[PDB]
Amino acid sequence: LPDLKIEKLDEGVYVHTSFEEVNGWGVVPKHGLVVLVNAEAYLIDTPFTAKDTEKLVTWFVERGYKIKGSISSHFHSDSTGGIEWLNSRSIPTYASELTNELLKKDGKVQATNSFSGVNYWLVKNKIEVFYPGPGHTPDNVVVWLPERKILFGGCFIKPYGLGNLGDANIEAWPKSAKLLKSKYGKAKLVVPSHSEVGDASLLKLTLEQAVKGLNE
Amino acid sequence: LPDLKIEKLDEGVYVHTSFEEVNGWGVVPKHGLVVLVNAEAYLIDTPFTAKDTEKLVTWFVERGYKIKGSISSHFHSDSTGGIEWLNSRSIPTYASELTNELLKKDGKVQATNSFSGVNYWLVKNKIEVFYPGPGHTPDNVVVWLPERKILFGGCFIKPYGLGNLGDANIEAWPKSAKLLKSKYGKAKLVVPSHSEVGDASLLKLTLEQAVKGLNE
Ligand SMILES: CN(C)c1cccc2c(S(=O)(=O)NCCCCNC(=O)CCS)cccc12
Ligand SMILES: CN(C)c1cccc2c(S(=O)(=O)NCCCCNC(=O)CCS)cccc12
Ligand SMILES: [Zn+2]
Ligand SMILES: [Zn+2]
Ligand SMILES: [Zn+2]
Ligand SMILES: [Zn+2]
């Protein structure tokens, strides 16, 4: 119900928040980022709908930035809901090979550009995509902004609880959460998809929740 | 297995941590406080055992502090484990009537002093005991320190999950959490029994966990 929000998080980094009604949760927020790189803008996850994605893109274009593309952290529509629109407007979309594979199987439009491997450099030294392994979804990846020490953890970061385990790999989440914690322990800010921005401690909390989750 | 820990949290306020092995959780920490009121020390919750309670009391006695009293947040042994030792040394012990009634049914030694009501002053205007209502247990109470705006949530504050529900009142917890949040939303620090120290946001998280728990 609430309208898309676009707030500055740090120099060249904005958080975009869109909303959706969830079973028993009420209206749940979804956070993504827009990273500025010299008159160029990059979307870290897209809003749920084409509407907000269009709104998001226009906000930045009307401010002088050229939308260079969007990268989605995992296949769920809260990260990929705007790929359909962006593609139809010939705006480059990116998703990991596992994400596109999951998207196709779920009857969803795929990102135009895909990648695989542990690391993927969208913008050398400015925007880096990391795959810690299966967790929330088999494909979840995180986005590391080296210059600001900011880590967008997406739906993988779950400090207060794992959430729906339907498409999750609870058996491997702890291992993945451990690798992520050791790779980005120096993060100044960790941005979750469904809860407040915090610090490197959300890495630890996510790991403990995964361990607790598997134990059950 | 880890040794009792005593760390300063703020002026005149220390956090004491004892440890236990907890079925499927590994070594779990238990936090309590020691509040200093002019050369006199007050224990907020005791360690699990007598030897640790002794270690705690001695740490402060050897520093010129008279142990003026200790209050237990609820009847479980992680809050009351040292009442026996303290009484044996004539150190004033406090617990609400409900806690004392539950301690009796548990065949445990009772606090020498009992109180009741929504709020009780262990030390007028310096240390407040608040009863939000049933939650983790039917008797859980919290301790508020007015000067430093520090709230010891005890085992009732569960921002990451409720924990064992065997002695809990899940139907009332959310109501109790609501009351605690509106009463202590001004807290600067909220100290849970089994997780890191945080701010007023732990109250909100707790409420949401209670709600989620009731629904589940
Ligand atoms: C209770 N309280 C501690 C919580 C606050 C914020 C988020 C919590 C989550 S969550 O972080 O999981 N977000 C809520 C569910 C959002 C559901 N959305 C989807 O499934 C969309 C695709 S990812 C899980 C458990 C608990 C959460
Ligand atoms: C996963 N991670 C986020 C967590 C960290 C710290 C505490 C968590 C709790 S908890 O805060 O509930 N305590 C953990 C079990 C403590 C066991 N000790 C007792 O039951 C003694 C009697 S009160 C619940 C869920 C999750 C917790
Ligand atoms: Zn998801
Ligand atoms: Zn999500
Ligand atoms: Zn307890
Ligand atoms: Zn406890």
Image (cartoon, coloured by chain):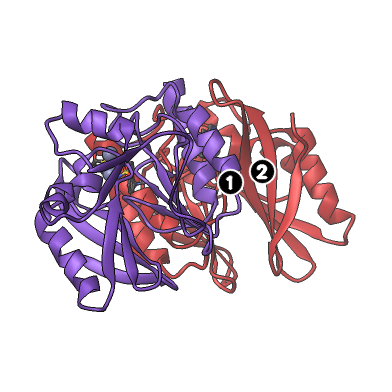
Chain colours: A purple, B red
In which quadrant of the rendered image does the C terminus of chain B lie?
Answer: top left
Q: How many numbered marks, from 0 up?
A: 2
Image position, residue B203 (x, y; %): 40, 56
Relative to A103, A123 lies left or right: right
Element on which disc 1 rests: loop
Quarter occupied by the N terminus of chain B:
top right
Chain of the residue displaying label 1: B
| Residue B72 numbered mark, or none | 1
Q: Neighbour class for label 2 at 10 Å: few (<14), some, many (≥20)?
A: many
- Residue B194 visible within the image: no
Kindly identify the residue that appears in the image at 51 percent across and 64 percent down: A148
Task: Find the distance from the CA under tag 2 to the CA under tag 1.
Answer: 7 Å
Is residue A128 in view?
yes
Among the two numbered marks 2 and 1 on one chain, the one whose residue lies closer to the N terminus: 2
Q: Are marks 2 and 1 in contact (CB under 8 Å)?
A: yes
Residue beneath label 2, please? B46
* As drawn, A119 above or below A210: below
The relative height of residue A51 versus residue A119 in the rendered view (above or below) is: below
| Disc 1 residue type (three-letter) | Ser
Query: Which residue is situated farthest in the right direction here?
Result: B62
- The residue nearer to you, when weighing A83 against B155, is A83
Dot 2: element: loop
Task: Choose top left, top right, bottom left or bottom right for residue B63.
Answer: bottom right
Q: Which x, y percent locates residue B47?
A: 68, 40
**Is A88 placed left or right of B148 in the picture?**
left
The x, y position of residue A177, in whole percent, is 50, 35
Q: Nearer the viewer, residue A37 or B9?
A: A37
Tag 2: residue type?
Thr
Q: Residue at x 45, y 24 (%)?
A: A172
Local packing at callout 1 (Cα closer than 10 Å; few below 14, some 14-19, many 20+) is: many
Which numbered circle lies on residue B141?
Answer: none
Residue A143 in percent (x, y) is at 42, 50
